[PDB]
Structure formats: structure tokens, C-alpha cells
Image (tube, rainbow, N blue to C red):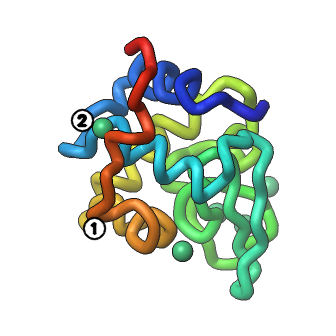
Amino acid sequence: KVFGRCELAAAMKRHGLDNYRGYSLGNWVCAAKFESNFNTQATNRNTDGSTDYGILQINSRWWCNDGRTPGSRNLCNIPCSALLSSDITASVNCAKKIVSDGNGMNAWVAWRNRCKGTDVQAWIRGCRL
Ligand SMILES: [Cl-]
Ligand SMILES: [Cl-]
Ligand SMILES: [Cl-]
Ligand SMILES: [K+]
Ligand code: NA
């Protein structure tokens, strides 16, 4: 599913991401924009053999099981395919664990390089929330 900007903002808010770990909703929407362009079916293969999945490009080295990342963990206790669903519940629940892991949203390199420090409120501007 390819979400609209305000549609995704509303879904993220319903699942408790707004201000989670102190990160406003615009931070999460901005991260999703540059990780996946709002597409739940986005995937990206990494040089180390791991793969990133879903609207927040969550990685199989630590967070989900795909059966093809030797030595990896599955800290969100889900198949990576669950991160590709049209329903964002699994991605949100796993993102909550990731952002609590110590480095906040710096866990998403694209957030650090493209959202951090910017006017992230623009990403929810105009949305009925
Ligand atoms: Cl915001
Ligand atoms: Cl497996
Ligand atoms: Cl980047
Ligand atoms: K594996
Ligand atoms: Na894994």
C-alpha cells in the first residue's frame, strides 16, 4: 500500500507514535517519506546481506526474521514479511522498540541525514489530526 502523507500521519497517531520517545509525528512521517516514499512494500538489500522492510525500512540484522541473514536476531519477534502489510501495526510496534534502543531516531540513517533538525512539522501541516 502507498499511503498518502496525511493518511499515514493519522495511522501513526492511532498506533501511538506521536511523541513516542519524545519524537513528534512529523519526525515519523519524514522518516517514512525518505525510507520508503510511504510504500509499505518497499524493500532494500544491504551489502552485508541483510534487508530493510516496509514503510520504515526495518532491518533483518536485528529486528525481524527473514531466514536469509546469517547470525541475525529477531528482536521484534516477527517475520520480516509482516512489515510489508497494508496494516502498519507491526511496523509501528517494532519501530517503538528500535527508537527505544539507545540512539533514538538516529537508528534511521535517512532520518539523521534528511529529517533531523529540519522543519518536520511541515510533514503534518494541513492534516486533520
Ligand atoms: Cl510534528
Ligand atoms: Cl525462516
Ligand atoms: Cl541518507
Ligand atoms: K536469518
Ligand atoms: Na533477523
The residue nearer to you, when weighing 62 against 112, is: 112
Q: Quadrant of the N terminus?
A: top right
Q: Which residue type carries mark 1?
A: Asn
Vertical relation: 66 (above or below) 82:
below
Q: Which residue type carries mark 2?
A: Asn
Disc 2/disc 1 C-alpha distance (Å): 16 Å
The residue nearer to you, when weighing 98 against 109, is: 109
Seen at 41% across and 32% down, the residue is 124
| Residue 2 screen position, x and y as percent | 75, 34
Of the image marks 2 and 1, the number of the one nearer the N terminus: 2
Seen at 39% across and 41% down, the residue is 122
Seen at 31% across and 52% down, the residue is 119
Q: Quadrant of the C terminus?
A: top left
Residue farthest to the top? 128
| Residue 76 screen position, x and y as percent | 51, 47
Location of mark 2 (residue): 19
Vertical relation: 2 (above or below) 66:
above
Q: Which quadrant would residue 85 be assigned to in this image? A: top right
| Residue 11 screen position, x and y as percent | 51, 21
| Location of ligand 3 given as a quarter of the image | bottom right
Location of mark 1 (residue): 103
Tell me the SS state at disc 2.
loop
Seen at 68% across and 62% down, the residue is 52
| Residue 96 screen position, x and y as percent | 38, 43
Drawn side of residue 126 relative to residue 67, left or right: left
